[PDB]
Image: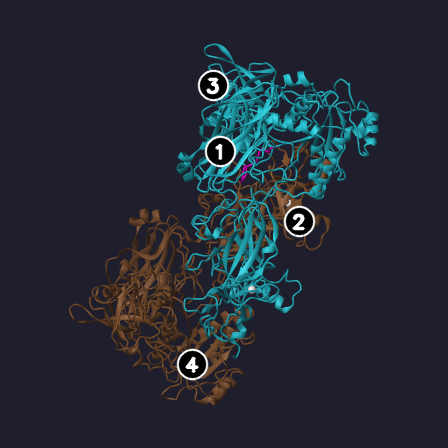
Chain colours: A cyan, B brown
Amino acid sequence: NDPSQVKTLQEKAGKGAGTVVAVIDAGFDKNHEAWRLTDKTKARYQSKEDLEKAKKEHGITYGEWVNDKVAYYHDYSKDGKTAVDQEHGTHVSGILSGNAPSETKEPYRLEGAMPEAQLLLMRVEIVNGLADYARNYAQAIRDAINLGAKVINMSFGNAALAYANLPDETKKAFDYAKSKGVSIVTSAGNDSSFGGKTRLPLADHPDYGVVGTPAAADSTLTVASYSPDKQLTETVRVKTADQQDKEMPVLSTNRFEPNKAYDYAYANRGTKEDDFKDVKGKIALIERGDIDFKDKIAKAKKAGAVGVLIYDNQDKGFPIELPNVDQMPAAFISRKDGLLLKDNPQKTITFNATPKVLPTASGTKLSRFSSWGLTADGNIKPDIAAPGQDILSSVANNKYAKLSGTSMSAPLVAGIMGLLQKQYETQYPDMTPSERLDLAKKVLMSSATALYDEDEKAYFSPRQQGAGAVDAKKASAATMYVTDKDNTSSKVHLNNVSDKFEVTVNVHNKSDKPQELYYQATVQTDKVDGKHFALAPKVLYETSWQKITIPANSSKQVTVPIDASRFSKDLLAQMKNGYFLEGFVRFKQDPTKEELMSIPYIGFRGDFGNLSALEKPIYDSKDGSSYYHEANSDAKDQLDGDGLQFYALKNNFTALTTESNPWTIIKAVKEGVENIEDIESSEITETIFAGTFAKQDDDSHYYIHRHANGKPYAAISPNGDGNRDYVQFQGTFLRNAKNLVAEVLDKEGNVVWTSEVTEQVVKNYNNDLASTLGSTRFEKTRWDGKDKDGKVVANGTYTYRVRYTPISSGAKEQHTDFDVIVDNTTPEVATSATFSTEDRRLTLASKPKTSQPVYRERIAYTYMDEDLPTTEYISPNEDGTFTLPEEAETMEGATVPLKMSDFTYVVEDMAGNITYTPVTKLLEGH
Amino acid sequence: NDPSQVKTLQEKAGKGAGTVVAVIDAGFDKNHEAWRLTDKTKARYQSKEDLEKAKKEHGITYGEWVNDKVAYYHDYSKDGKTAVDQEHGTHVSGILSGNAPSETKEPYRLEGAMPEAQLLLMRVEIVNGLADYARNYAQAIRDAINLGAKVINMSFGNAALAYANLPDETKKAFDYAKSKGVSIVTSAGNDSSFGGKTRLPLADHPDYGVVGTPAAADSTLTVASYSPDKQLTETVRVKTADQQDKEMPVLSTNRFEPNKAYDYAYANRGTKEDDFKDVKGKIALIERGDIDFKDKIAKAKKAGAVGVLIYDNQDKGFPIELPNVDQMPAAFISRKDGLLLKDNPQKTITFNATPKVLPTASGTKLSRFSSWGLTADGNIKPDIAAPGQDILSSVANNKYAKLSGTSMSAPLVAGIMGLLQKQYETQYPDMTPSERLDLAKKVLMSSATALYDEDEKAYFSPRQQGAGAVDAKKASAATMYVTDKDNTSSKVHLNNVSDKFEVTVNVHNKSDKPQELYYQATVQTDKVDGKHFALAPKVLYETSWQKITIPANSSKQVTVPIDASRFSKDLLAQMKNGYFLEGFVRFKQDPTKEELMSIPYIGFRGDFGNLSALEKPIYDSKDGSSYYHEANSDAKDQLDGDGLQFYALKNNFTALTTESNPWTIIKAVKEGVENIEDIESSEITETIFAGTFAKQDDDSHYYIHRHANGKPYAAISPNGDGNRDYVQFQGTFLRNAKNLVAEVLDKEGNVVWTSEVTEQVVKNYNNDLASTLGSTRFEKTRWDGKDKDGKVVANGTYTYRVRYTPISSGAKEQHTDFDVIVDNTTPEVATSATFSTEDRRLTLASKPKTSQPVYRERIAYTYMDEDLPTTEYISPNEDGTFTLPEEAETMEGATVPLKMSDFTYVVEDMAGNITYTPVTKLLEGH
Ligand SMILES: [Ca+2]
Ligand SMILES: [Ca+2]
């Protein structure tokens, strides 16, 4: 079980004896290691003393020690009250103790290729700001270096750091690590597509990679994990009708009885009752689907119980780790096999205690949601891929299956590069540590082999696999390597390209003899599924092999012309705003032999820098829906606001917000009332969307109102009463942006106001409280209807303009305009009315006169129901009169008499201008 | 225009000169009344002096003289701030003045058939309780009598008095008027069917009459209003194709210019532009429907129409008073006339100046929603019917069209009887005022002609028209009359009856000659439309005419056998809980001549007294719906409670209520924080329905949960924490009841607790804030889980029984049972847990162990989003662990870090037993 083939490298450079490896994480509780045994004490840090002395010569104070292997374990971001289990048995169990064996099924460790090296475990977590988490991290790596690690494995715990802007103490640490030839290695990420695992990016928005690691943290290598076409797995033997044994892969939760002969009974999907017809003593065989695992396992235990065998309902699916439901032993198996047992004559099986490396149902596979990413300048983010168990966990959370068993992929590559760099210390004695680190990185990427997606008959995108799957055997034997034209990077980025472009790479031959090679370039784009990217590769073509010879101790450039014009029409119909044209320039000794070297390249057929950064306003949605917001069918322009209880996860789209303030609160303020919190009325101040209005006869909903031209009726009355006084920008950003600023322009076109600027905008790549919500409200963009250093603007129509710039180099500034009406005209309403006691009808002396059309004209009254205030509203009759009830009924059956003094006439216009008048006032003499 | 034919009675008894007519009402502002004139000041009261003298002799210190007509006026309920105009113009415009002429199309007014009588106007209104209202009313009639009334018209303004229990004072007042031969007449009401004009009564609940006037009133006569087959009306004329003039009825709002030819154009229903294309300068002819009148008119005016003619979409509809929209002339016409105009080649019309008596489109008609009513003992409520303009108003309110122009019907009858009683002063010299009144009532009702409903080929139900339509001519000329078997009443009620029964009535011959007549009985029931009563009659059959001779000056009993067994099968299929068998015993001097006398009778084929008084609990609705509540298709079990803001008109059905109290408040109370609306949490105490629960992963709705037996999962944890501590009865009563009481029985059938009694229950005859809600919450029935001695009852299952008794005589007590489990077992939960800083999961050591099944098992935390606390909940993963986030994001894109001290483990079972433990507590070094 050696996928990356490190054997030859170890034979050549060793296994890390006398070396030190640093591992920085949020925690190491899940040791994975059997609390990692020990070794063969033959080099450095052989005792507390050994540590202390060095640790003191280097000016280090907080150093610890845990035994051999783990020669260090200081805890940064310490203060915060920690209580693992029993605290190592209460003070290390009276000093000297602590251990936990077992490492079954796990093929790789926290060293991969350097198992005989000591570890420096530095725990670092976010406690009191990223800025301080960053400084700890920087110190955490400077100490590793001063402690002599040469190899550092970094993980940022529970992410949420995507696009974070940390202090320069961080980048400073990285530069220093680079200067000393120390490698910093991190993981590429398993949830890297815009929208998250529960969604797919839209085909017209190709900028969908989400980089989890902050730019400042430029690690030596970012590595993606993948599942090889074969893996070390537990198994279960079965006898087929033809009378023969068939050993199959299985993932089990809870342990079965080693070597038995369990009987098994099919139960469909366990969604019905007759499904577990028996199961009496039979293991429940169930197909995945319709309902969740927890239930399948529970229903199985109800009946016969014993154990269960759930089989995937997807062909090339990853093995799923079942939940532990009442110690119930549950194992997961591929679909193929599942369908095999469902027909096997002898419904009997045996669980082998011998893990065996067998083919995988998935075959060579990278999760469709993993690694996707581009750097600010156009380079693909991931550098290389490495093997991992890659199992989908059904218990990471209750929202989606989280990819698991990938944490050991980056460390594997780290170990391999440490050994290769070591190999170079003897192979190229004159090189400095930095130079050896650079060479090792270039060779590792060049020699890495491009993974193939059999399922799509295409290579996995370099945006996912980087330069390819690490191959230690090739790296160690490598006497040549390929870089881009600049001779600095091991990846090529072309930025914007037309249908015809050239890819030029440089082959560096370090051997004393010329080398003959064959080269080709593969060309591919993205696969689309309707209006969404499928997150799968789409091969276009590959060039036919060309021969070239590189003279001894020299380098030669290779240029491969590419022409994908014949695919333009079809591809544009699927991805109208452009698409990627990417691939690999591959080299071989002979076209029939295996890939010797490969370097990835990527171009964008369009103008990537200028792709739209903001999702259009929901007002513009012909459907009423948006990427993160579902519309209400059977409700044209319904667009409720925050309501009485806001849900951060709802209404996440581009729009303008404003506030609704009921006349009751407005009046309470104009009077005195300090409290207002317990006023005898049921309405509250609410945040709503501009352009939306409640119905005359409220129905608890707000609706978008539009002008004859289709634009939303946005209007404010900046008169300080809090009712629709301002508009504020809320946006769903599809791409990162900078310098977001709002400005207001009058009819002429003059800028009368400019907001403060929001330096950085982070795209809304998900809609989750733990990472980022689907939209963001920008308070600095709020416009209260006033001009630059001045007063309220004059009534009229204005242009509320939101400006923002994509971060891509040279990107043009983008903007979205909203027409906003300003109007502070108080409504003119009747000064008198008459009331018919026989008719209970109030007749106003005249209709309301407002500058903006009438929004609502009602008669309000409030009555108590069990100390619970309730404000009722009366709409006008067809002739403009209002009928006033003589009473209101309580839910308990009590009659509440109503008098003229209980009623208040309220008129509100579209801009929120409002006037309220006691009906007694209208009736009195004049 | 004398539909009641009062001509012959007047030219034999006069027109009320020298008499006094009293009118008690809530107002008179609408009272047109041709006041001022009297053309013979030789009335009972000449000048203020004669009046002031009269009231001085009867201890009346209040009241004032006005006009030679209206010799007395007074407001028995001043104080409370009630303003009219400007005091007639600052003290009756200089003291002693006035004028407000404006009456047309009306052949009737106050005083009725006694235009020469003086008036006594008593203004009474509900002001500070119905008790004060009652006294004020009793006093008003007392003053009326002493001032020499003889006739008293009573109007209770805007009721909401249905089934009100007024003081024994009011009754004494009536008994006094009765003893003085003073008749008190009142209207039968135009909205008398269960559920209101907006609904229809259900066919399986035949007790659907709603009596608006309090029982402790009992007028001399309760008058129903009806539209005759011809009415005085303004008209319009058109030239038909035969070249002749066609004059048709019209009801106009605002005014068209008389004798001026107007062109008109058809606009369909005016529900779509282009409809008004050829309308400019013409009258828009528009059909009723789809949109409201106001909009059809506004659209017409915008299109340049000079007025509109709206025609009915109903064939026998009442004319409709159109709304005044910007003074637009608007006239309403029948369907037939509208179709005639639409199809007329010469589209020119002229509005005539002189009104005219013309056939009505409705024909003889009683509103389908009017009069329905029975008294407690089973008598039909209405006594007689009288003509009115009966016009539907589209501006009375904004929910339904209100029948108008019925106010003069009762006063008309009052005047007729006043005259008949005067007539009896001469003939029948020794009778006493009391005996004259009783004879007048008998003759008036016997003489009344049973109205025929041509549309249904059946007589209108006696429950609507009483003894028939008043006919002063037959009344005045009558020398005979029929009464029930006794001589007490002029109405017959048989209570419960089988298919075969007989009706016996007494004919009284006051003549000196033998009288030969023919008689028969009509038999009818209710017309049904699917699941509802159509509020229309269903004729069954009429008996063959039989002969009888009544000797001079004597009485003779007449019996008519009724056999409707032939119809039971069908009728029972439509009205399964029984149906009425009613009709009239009619008398003629010749089967081919007109009706001379008729007396109504009514029986109920079934057991009326024991009809179900309470709608079954919503839990039992297969649909999820009830009479006043529509279920949610797609979720029959959804049953939300009051929520964040209760709606008096929603969720009105029979059920049990309880309360939900979040742990945050339970904790805040258990600790001691005064003022609960300050706590840093978003949830609040909510009223919900027992048997309902939120989902583990809250979706903002509550759902009914049921035991396997199908009963709602009603459970309480009587431990004083406010969370599901009690159950309270909420009922939608279909019939009035008395002595409502709740009791709880243990498994043994023993009563362990009894609630206070709720003496009277008024049926929920509507779902309207101004009259009655669709259900009533009975707080006295609240059970907090304690027994008769304040001791919390033991955990177990109990029967929450609600008992109540219909008001019908002999009715058995009915009851509804609800199974309620009581369980105060505190949940037992893990006391320790381990948290993985790596996986981010919190693993609990054990449990949860609860007595009742688990309701919700969650981890909560609250963060701020702009000084707005928001409590978030995390559900467990499929293996029982919980994943805890590191941060929460604000809507403004800010990061709110989360630490262990922020999380709380909360366990709640089905009875509301709950436990909450800080996650830090569970971690507390174990
Ligand atoms: Ca305002
Ligand atoms: Ca409780």
Q: Kindly report the distance in space between the C-alpha atoms of the residues bearing marks 4 and 3.
A: 102 Å
Tell me which numbered mark, 1 or 3, is placed earlier along the sequence: 3
Magenta residue span: A188-196
Horizontally, is B435 left or right of B131 in the view?
A: left
Q: Residue visible at 55% across and 32% down? A: A464
Secondary structure of residue under mark 4: strand
| Residue carrying label 2 | B665
Q: Kindly report the distance in space between the C-alpha atoms of the residues bearing marks 1 and 3.
A: 50 Å
Report the mark closest to the observer, 1 or 3: 1
Q: Quadrant of residue A126?
A: top right
Q: Residues within 10 Å of mark 3 (few under 14, many from 20)?
A: some
- Find out whether the residues at labels 1 and 3 contact each other: C-beta distance under 8 Å: no
Question: Where's residue B186, x and y in %?
Answer: 42, 70
| Residue carrying label 4 | B119
| Ligand 2 image position (quadrant) | top right
Q: Are marks 1 and 3 on the same chain?
A: yes
Of residues A255 and A736, the one nearer the viewer is: A736
| Residue carrying label 3 | A340
Question: Where's residue B529, x and y in %?
Answer: 34, 52
Q: Kindly report the distance in space between the C-alpha atoms of the residues bearing marks 4 and 1.
A: 109 Å
